[PDB]
Every structure is written in C-alpha cells, then in structure tokens.
Length: 330
Image (cartoon, rainbow, N blue to C red):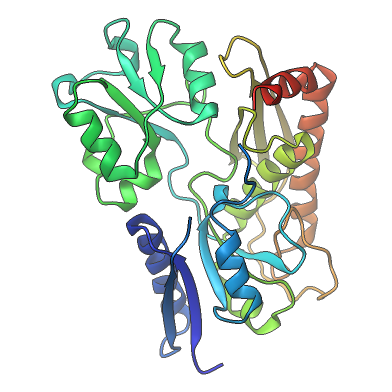
C-alpha cells in the first residue's frame, strides 16, 4: 500500500484520538507510513458522526477511520466493519464544577443547582438519582461547554465523559467521577473503534494488532445488549461491564426520559480473557459489526450471548413499554 491513509473528523478531540491510534500503530509497525486525512463533517439521523467518513472509505479515499466506539451504531452498513477495539480508557461519566464549587460533588450541591447535560441517558439517570437538582440542556464542543459553565453563571456543573476531558489534557477539571449507581455509561464509552472496509484483508490484518481482548469482550456484550433492545439515540439505555475473577459482569438499564421509570439488572458469564492470538477463517461473520478474527471466537460469542440474555430479561420485565413511550416523545 506504500501509504496507509487514516480518516478523521476535524474536531480537536477527534484529531487527538486519531493521533493516539496512529502512534500505537507506528509502535507496532515502525517505518510504515501513515497519512492523516481530516474530513469536514456535520433524533432523526442514525449515524451523524460516521456517514461521510464511511463514504470516503467506500471510495478508497482513506483506509481506516478512528471513532469513539460509542459513536458507531450497533448495525453498520454492509460494506464496513470495526476492525479494532482499542484498550478502554476511563469509561465513566464525570462532573466538572463551576470554580466557585471546587471541592463539591453532585450530592453536596445546593438544591436547585443547575447541571448542564444534553444527553438523554445522562439526564434520565441523574434526574432519578438527584430529584432536586435541575438538569438543563447545554450545547457546544468541550471548550464551549466549559466556557458556558465558568462564566454565564447559569450552570453549577456540567456532565461530560471522563475520557473526553482527559484526552483534551483537562484531567484537572474532572471534579467527580460518577459511579455506576449514580450514572452508568453509554454503550462503548471510553473505547476507540477503528472502522475499515469489511473485505479489505490487508488493512484488517494491520489494525488487528490494536484489539484489546478484555475491551473487545466488554464492548461486544454492551453492543449486543443495546442491539437486541434496539435502543437507538431516542431511548435512555446504559451499561456497566467488568471482567474479574474469570467472570464478565454486564449491568444494563433502560429509563424513561425523566428517569422515573427504570428497569436495570445484572447478569454474568464465565469468560476467560484470551491471552493468545489466532488466524481465524475469513468467512466467520462479524459480531455486532466487529471483526476480530485474530482473537479466539468462543469468548466473543459468549459475550454477545450475555448481552442478548440481559436484553431478554429486561424485555420480560417491561423494557419495551419504556422504550416505546420514550421514543413516542421523538
């Protein structure tokens, strides 16, 4: 190929994520040449962050694209796949407090404090957990939301992903990291995913070195849960996964938009984090849009099965009524 072309969105955070994956690639493949191509990008739309870069992949204008994994739908268009799931960075949601409120938590904020978040998932869960704080929409990239917090005196705090603040070099602004019992994260949050042409074997070979087995298994379970619920962007759905002591634990929840209705449950499966790589057959189907033929397939299937199992438990307890009501609210 002589040159590997890497597509990226133009935002600073997207460019930093892309550079971090390219740096890892260069550490495995010293001397290999990489070329970063940043493309102008943009309810309703199902893949706001991915369509234009997918078109560049389809026209062989780039060879791989770096995304936040949570920005990739659980069903991709048929000519694409996720060829790498990188080792997870911190998946949790985070609170940034107005400078006047340094030392606080959401639990010690005065009642009626205004907390900025535009995420349905975050807003449902935090309204349930903090019924006397006011959760109000806020718009902007990371820099803009920080400025709105620090100045216009409207917001006492904002909710952002920990990983986003850390990639921007703003670790010091993370004032509180929310536990799962306070706010479970989005499916895939904190993991980077690399999207490629589904039958481009050369590139799938190269990027397979980036797969982190523990993160791959966790993200397969989370994505399989969300896919079986068909949560989309209009319904609050959230997860927590952990691999410990030979088990994969998946917690999954659905909420009404105001957080007053909720179903949440935890299942576990015995799944060993594979330490060996493999050269698996090319015709094995992708799992929830992910190609990882160099990672043993047994555990991946077991993780997908855990996600389906948990979604089915939630459906048997009424999740479809919550989803339908939330989605009727467009």
